[PDB]
Image (tube, coloured by chain):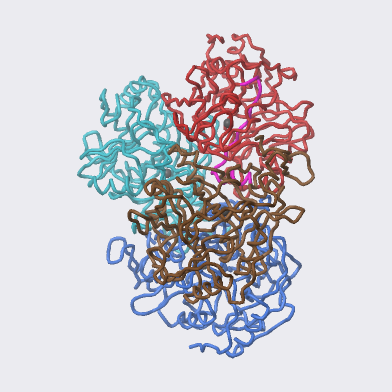
Chain colours: A blue, B cyan, C red, D brown
């Protein structure tokens, strides 16, 4: 269990960007800029800085050329400069390794703190950032599948209750989760900005980054991305969806970039800003909890996730999840799921829904 | 092979309605009227007459209470009264059993001819029909998943080339089909009204009715139907989709009514009215031919289909398809499919795409 | 009045393209290609050939450099080559001027007939046309405001009943019209292809081309066009809309190109292929007849229209309309229009709706 | 000028509900429930409590039967119960009239404070509220024009800079405003919850409530509202729109209820939660500032607004605006507005855009 520090927690505003190491910068560029239409804030032979349509801070994604594809940093912007200090004292009290550069680790970012948090994830906290032209009304640049905002991250970690508690102490509030009757927690969504989540914990071997998610204005914007991937003959890069999530109620799509980093295009979840926002708990066996329409969750979604780096550039060692696997308890040979609780009709046993 | 009659073929306008036998009228009513929102033109204890939002003829669907769920008639409206006679002479020349009632077989229809066509399907041809209020502008009745028109039928039959030829002689023109390099034809789409199809042939054991299809105005109308089925906890009744078809380029969804009759909600295919409309032929192994995004085609889609009746009310005997099964050659243990022709990467062998 | 020829009418399929004379090729290209995203089938220093997203014939619009902006030809495609011959004989029996070129009048068209019809409009009939790549599934090229097909033309002529009889004899069927309780007809819509219209007659001084119309897949594609024009600071070139039409029930938008040729973006009207399709007749004073939401019709919409050229390139003399003018009768000094028949609330006397 | 209290301001979360006095409960119910589809949380012969689709607090709108249609209270929810106490002390230090009821002023609300603020508006602060069923996934109840959340209020006050300072001291942050090259401010938008605004100040005679605003998921949901109103022959109750706002970039529509209270349907504005969110300032003469497409702003939109009641139920005296009026300065006899700064084309002198 992770202790609650005496030091006051920093006031986190929202997830702001992620820095991903990629192996071939040109292929990645083609995927992110040519296929997805993200806007370049800056680029050189080692990195590409990307921002979504409505963003004003410098970037929501940093592609960094490297030998091994992995997550290098997931960054949260804090409310004031002083919160960067509060973050430094907070993680030191927790005994975590931290590093601080008064002029940032990446272009366009100012004073920043990076840490190997208790779950082994490289987190960044910063306030100062370079403002860039906010393209929210540049309709002459609007593509049919325009990505408008960065919305959340999703982390794969072994013990969800352990991570939940630590993030709750950090100020994130849980909006939805998934449990079973034997007391096992499989996943939790937590927020800071007022949407369903800024980050989430998915139970599994970790530390690993499950995905980064961007949102679109409307559902047809997500449909366009699939259509365009079909036209480009890269539909094998569409991993799952599109669909309507049960948890978070958002319309979604998961695709894979050149190095297998998973990207989620998401839209239309609901407001959670009120402090007494009602928490929704879903049963792991409810076949409408992940996909509201009952579609099977592809197995690679549960098994495949990106590696993460420590502050030295090395890949973090992966810890095995000891609790029940969501995949095993639902689509494994000894798992089951239902459409209607207690109704054998429309339920599945040791088999995925829809005949697979 | 089916001979081309000397008698002139009737001028068929479009598919107009289908009469389906159902086992429990109240359950079926709940599905078609309460869930799907079709509009009642008339109903009594034995039948329910339904029409879509923009229809002016009496009905696009007739639910008839019966002991065995099956297709009783798929009806095409012809251009003039005289075409009903031309249809009578045409099928008699073909040696088919025909029946004709100067006042229709169902309410709201006038002089009509029903036949057991060369493929064993009960076809109806009629001109006269009762006009009803056209609801195209009754926005006060518009539901979020409004079905606006009846678009096509899809027939399951053993020998596609055999049926194609007969329908071509009847005046339908082929817009798209699916073949392989060994000369096997798996399916064909043919039209009369200017859209991709009024009917289609799907290779398999038959005669069987694969599905009836309705269209919506926009793609979000189709999304709403899935969402509503999730809210009602009947997502197990969603068989496949939604998706973008490769063939026909339409956005689609397949759902199952209480008796397993398959309904397709479809939208936005293209114009085919020009006589030299370019025909598109797809390779059976192209994984983007059915679902443009690469999603696996659920096996029940290929195996399950509705029974059809002869003119006496008996179920037609089913003939086995002798040619290669589309399911076997693509997702069977000895089948394969590709994303990019000639690229092993993104191809599937004895396994369905997406991990199933 | 215009006589019904003895010669059989040609079999018309649909409106196929319009040839417009523009004064500055570069500016027009900017509008039609960069702003609207139409696709270039061919271009040189004198002309630009554009086609919509789902078209397979050579083009839907020909921009020709000339000294006076005007309409040079509105082309309809006929069913067979012989129909061109039938069209020639038909117009000759009408005593109209004809001109035939077996090699066509513009690139991409073959044997074709151009005539100066009875209403003074330059109509072209043709069958042969060079097939080009149908871009209907090129989602990698799909813009957020993609124009997918050419839908109709709209002509301004002095006497509507007169032109109507002529076009009905030619095979066009009226779907909707606007009249007053005194028999004066203000406008008629007629089709060949099964949508509300291929062309329409708007009462006013003519001959003049009121507008050419393209359609999109969904309503949001039309919103994008408006949004993009705002971003490019050319919102003054948006004349009227977006709105919902009363007549035709389609979502619409009217914009002006560099020489003031009016272009309508249009979507989702209904099926009219059945020969007994019910005709709708709106009263001219009904304020929901043109814009279903009661938005006022801009004055220029009734007064400004494009000039038409005779076969020698001269501008056709304009004949004054003698019957009541729709503008005067509804939004003029002594105009009147209502929301509900007989209700004083929601009615407008001598002014437009909404306070203008 | 209004003094900045010494007492700490209460922590405001978002606008939560408006209590409107209506003269005929039955007619208003028809409008808000049957026409708009808002959900009834509770009702009796004197009041109707309505909530939007995704709300979990008791209600977003209270319709109260009374003799003079007016605004009785605009309520903001605060972070904690103690914030109510903080609000009371804050307003008392301002010398404003306060009234507190530990049992609340309307059903479903607990301890609450109502005050007659410095601008003469009846504001309510509260934390406790009865939780009800969050209908966010009840797709079986989702209408084609579903209102999903309450978004903002809009107040008409004489002096904008004055009210702005007061609200900034209260914790609101300005996101956008409209000014002229002469320092006169015409309107300001300010938020607490991270969207463009929770409330706004429109210059004009006040206090008056300009409108309450709800949002939808997508643009087509707003189109449906317009279409439905046309079907119900009440299009005269559509005041302005639909359009795209310049300020806020949201898709919008303004309708009038039975007593003429203005309701705005609104969607897709952007994120403003970061404390250094860039402020946008539009020039009053810029014709794309209110309607991005340059459509004219209806006169009544600037002159008509709802009355507000003091805490005793009397109508608040209305103070005349002394600064230039936005209407006069842009569409009046000596008004002026432009599409492009300095360009004579697309500019309007002494008249509205589009010819009115
Ligand atoms: Fe996610
Ligand atoms: Fe189909
Ligand atoms: Fe038109
Ligand atoms: Fe507003």
- Residue in front for this viewpoint, B354 or A190: A190
- Residue in front for this viewpoint, B226 or A337: B226
- Residue B157 can be seen in this image: yes
Q: Which residue range is magenta in the image?
A: C204-226
**Magenta segment includes C206:** yes
Q: Is residue A29 left or right of residue B38?
A: right
- Residue B238 can be seen in this image: no
Residue B249, compared with residue C42, is above or below; it is below
Q: Position of residue B180 (x, y in %)?
A: 49, 47
Q: Position of residue C80 (x, y in %)?
A: 56, 23
Q: Is residue B305 left or right of residue C173?
A: left
**Magenta segment includes C333:** no
Q: Position of residue A33 (x, y in %)?
A: 67, 59
Residue under the image location 33 percent in, 21 percent down: B85
- Residue in front for this viewpoint, A72 or A111: A111
Quadrant of image for the N terminus of chain C: top right
Q: Is residue D242 left or right of residue A280?
A: right
- Residue in front for this viewpoint, B209 or A307: A307
Q: Position of residue B134 (x, y in %)?
A: 39, 33
Residue D137, compared with residue C173, is above or below; it is below
Q: Is residue C349 left or right of residue A340?
A: right
Quadrant of image for the C terminus of chain C: top right
């Amino acid at each position: 269990e992770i202790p609650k520090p005496v030091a006051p927690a920093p006031d986190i505003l929202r997830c702001a960007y992620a820095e991903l190491v990629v192996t071939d910068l040109a292929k990645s560029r083609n995927f992110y800029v040519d296929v997805l239409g993200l806007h370049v804030s800056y680029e050189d032979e080692n990195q590409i800085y990307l921002r979504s349509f409505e963003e004003f801070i410098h970037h929501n994604l940093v592609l960094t050329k490297g030998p091994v594809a992995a997550l290098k940093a997931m960054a949260f912007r804090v409310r004031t400069p002083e919160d960067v200090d509060k973050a430094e004292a907070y993680y030191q009290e927790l005994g975590c390794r931290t590093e601080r550069r008064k002029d940032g680790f990446v272009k366009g970012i100012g004073d920043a703190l990076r840490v190997e948090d208790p779950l082994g994830f490289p987190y960044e906290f910063f306030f100062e950032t370079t403002h860039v032209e906010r393209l929210h009304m540049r309709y002459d640049l609007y593509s049919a599948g325009e990505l408008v905002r960065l919305d959340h991250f999703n982390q794969v970690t072994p013990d969800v209750p352990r991570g939940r508690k630590y993030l709750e102490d950090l100020g994130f509030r849980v909006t939805e989760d998934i449990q079973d009757d034997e007391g096992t927690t499989y996943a939790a969504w937590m927020h800071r900005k007022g949407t369903v989540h800024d980050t989430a914990l998915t139970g599994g071997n970790g530390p690993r980054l499950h995905h980064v998610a961007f949102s679109t204005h409307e559902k047809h914007n997500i449909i366009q991305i699939c259509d365009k991937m079909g036209a480009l003959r890269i539909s094998d890069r569409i991993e799952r969806g599109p669909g309507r999530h049960g948890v978070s109620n958002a319309f979604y799509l998961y695709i894979l970039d050149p190095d297998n980093h998973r990207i989620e295009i998401y839209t239309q979840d609901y407001y959670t800003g009120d402090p007494d926002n009602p928490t929704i708990t879903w049963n792991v066996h409810d076949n409408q909890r992940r996909d509201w329409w009952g579609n099977p969750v592809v197995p690679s979604w549960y098994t495949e996730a990106s590696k993460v780096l420590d502050l030295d550039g090395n890949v973090q060692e992966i810890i095995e999840r000891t609790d029940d696997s969501e995949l095993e308890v639902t689509i494994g040979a000894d798992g089951f799921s239902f459409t209607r609780a207690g109704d054998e009709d429309g339920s599945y046993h040791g088999q995925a829904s829809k005949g697979f």
